[PDB]
Amino acid sequence: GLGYGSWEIDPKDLTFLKELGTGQFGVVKYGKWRGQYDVAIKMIKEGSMSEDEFIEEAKVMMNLSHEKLVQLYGVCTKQRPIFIITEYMANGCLLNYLREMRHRFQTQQLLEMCKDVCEAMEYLESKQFLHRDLAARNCLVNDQGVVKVSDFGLSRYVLDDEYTSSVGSKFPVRWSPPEVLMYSKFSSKSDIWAFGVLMWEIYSLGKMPYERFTNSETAEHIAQGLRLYRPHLASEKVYTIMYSCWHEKADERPTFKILLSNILDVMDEES
Ligand SMILES: Cc1c(NC(=O)c2ccc(C(C)(C)C)cc2)cccc1-c1ccnc2nc(-c3ccc(C(=O)N4CCOCC4)cc3)[nH]c12
Image (cartoon, rainbow, N blue to C red):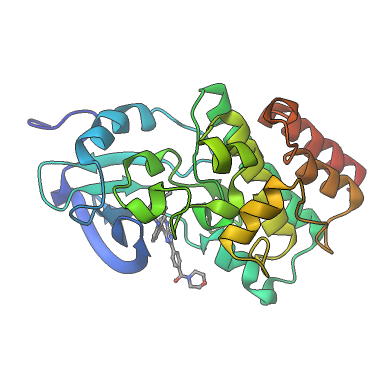
């Protein structure tokens, strides 16, 4: 309507129904858009986001459409707090989902979660778009058990120093390759490394990577060429795929297109 761009949702079209929790930008609620369509609504806490830079990027992010990406539907900018409207995922974050032992997951289900994530990441890679914080905590699960990648690229707009500094308390040390920890060298290959750690989280049913180490000790371990080792539920072929993501040389790490082909081959082998 009048006074609203293509990236703009009228907050009057929202019905707030339940609190979902709190993320880096504050409270997130479940609601309906125009009384019918399920949405998740991020209420952006004041001082948490580089809002003007995000709004300029929101336009591009809304065009990132893939069935395995948690869709950005629009933004509510003509206010304070600003809202980010996204697809709603009924089963919540993947990390908590993995930790629920009631699911009694089969390894074929765990491989399907890896494939869902890999398809989303191949799509982002095809658009030269980095996630920047790929991990099980940044994946969500829908009512059909499909895993989708969430909040891709939003790390760029976080104003929190503890999250942005590589030695910060909230920085994703355990999902970072040596070149990020040593030189701040971010690339498609740092998303590849993080994907390998995510496959390890899936096959480990949500254990924390390097669980007996601090972040400082993890950075040292990785720098010395040491790695996570095989989760009990991962076959040798699955372990070979996640391990390939951790090559010390970033240029020797696979692309998401190659990882997708490896995962499909293993699904065919372990059918
Ligand atoms: C995504 C999300 C965030 N994170 C963030 O905004 C956020 C922002 C920034 C970042 C960077 C920048 C660091 C990368 C990361 C992250 C925070 C809160 C809710 C949701 C959320 C969105 C979309 N859909 C969602 N669905 C949930 C849900 C929750 C609980 C149950 C629940 O209560 N259950 C009970 C029974 O067991 C499991 C489900 C069911 C469903 N939650 C959702």
